[PDB]
Image (cartoon, rainbow, N blue to C red):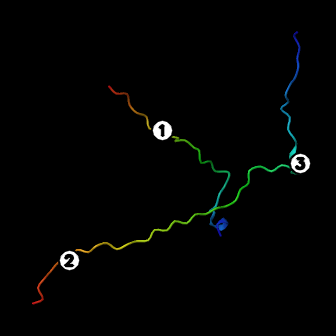
């Protein structure tokens, strides 16, 4: 059934998390 | 003529009788069908002898 197709969900997890180690672009000399 | 004439409140009901329900959730599913055709051949004529 369409409802059984729904995969495991878990409110504990956040899906809006930003990058924790962003790329730092060196200044152009 | 300086006076306060009216106001609006920010009150709300406590929905303990569940009179109000909000947006409803239901599951949906879509199916997409992609049949694979064959395409024109290329051949290699050769002699049978």
In this view, B40 is above or below A26: below
Q: Quadrant of residue A27?
A: top left
The label on residue B43 is 2
Alpha carbons under labels 1 and 2: distance apart: 55 Å
Task: Kindly identify which chain the residue marked by label 2 belongs to.
Answer: B
Determine whether, in the image, residue A3 is placed left or right of residue B48: right
Q: In front of the other: label 3 or label 2?
A: 2
The label on residue B16 is 3
**Label 2 packing within 10 angstroms: few (<14), some (14-19), many (20+):** few
Residue drawn 83% across and 32% down? B10
Alpha carbons under labels 3 and 2: distance apart: 77 Å
Residue occupied by mark 1? A22
Q: Quadrant of residue A2?
A: bottom right
**Residue B43 in the image: x percent, y percent?**
20, 77
Task: Kindly identify which chain the residue marked by label 1 belongs to.
Answer: A
**Residue B44 in the image: x percent, y percent?**
17, 78
């Amino acid at each position: 059934t369409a409802d059984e197709m729904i995969t495991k969900v878990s409110d504990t997890k956040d899906l809006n998390v930003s990058t924790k180690k962003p790329h730092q672009i060196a200044d152009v000399p | 003529d300086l006076a306060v004439i009216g106001f609006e409140l920010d009150t709300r009901f406590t929905n303990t009788n569940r009179r109000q329900r909000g947006h409803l959730l239901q599951t949906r599913a879509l199916q997409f069908r992609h049949p694979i055709p064959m395409h024109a051949p290329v051949t290699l004529p050769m002699d049978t002898m």
